[PDB]
Length: 271
Ligand SMILES: NC(=[NH2+])NCCC[C@H](N)C(=O)O
Image 1 (cartoon, helix red, strand yellow):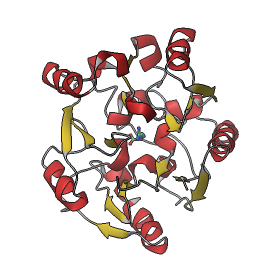
Image 2 (cartoon, helix red, strand yellow):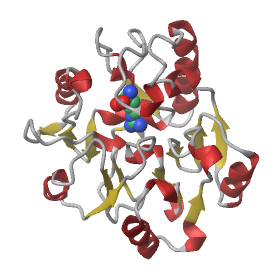
Image 3 (cartoon, rainbow, N blue to C red):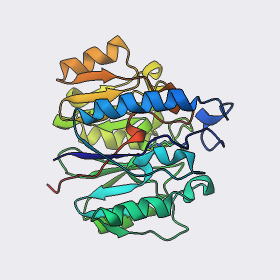
């Protein structure tokens, strides 16, 4: 069974600016359109996986972005500790959901930021965990995660403020494929990626797709769900065996997130 956690946009707005996509967008989201877009995404994901919901909290508009609730492996979750006070109030609500749903929760020190699956994505065969740092999660959190979850952690440094979470520019896929935007990473981190993923398994995104959040994609088996995709990228994905489903998420891009950011896979098998 594959299960994905989402959180509906009952209280969604753009109320502050903590990433560059939010600049100029305060109160520019339409709550009604956001509901419509989220409902279409929810339906599309539910066609591929079970969807669980956590009740949203008023005053925490970014709670829709459940990718940042924590990092799940098996029965364990490393709870996120947000870098910004504007999201720290989500933490007790996410903790309560994990506890109520049978997970055993690990908490980092309150001074050590780490933003969950948004910044840390497993290689889909379970060989290691790719973990971003540079804007939200601290590099020093990576050894904690490695030990708590008994996984090798491969740290990747983000260098572009637009691509401030790993999942905005990097997406492990089924079959060992990796969908990513190399310019979001420094040279050393690109070499680290390249050492592990050979060219035939790389699906390299160009900037025009990256800025439409193409890497912020939900992949269940051979299905990939995203906001918008160029024909060029759709054909590359089709050639690699994936079926692309697009669903519009413009109201969430105003807050710096798209399809993947609105999801957390809570069934991450031990392999
Ligand atoms: N996993 C993600 N890409 N999350 C996007 C979160 C967007 C939210 N406004 C923030 O700045 O934190």
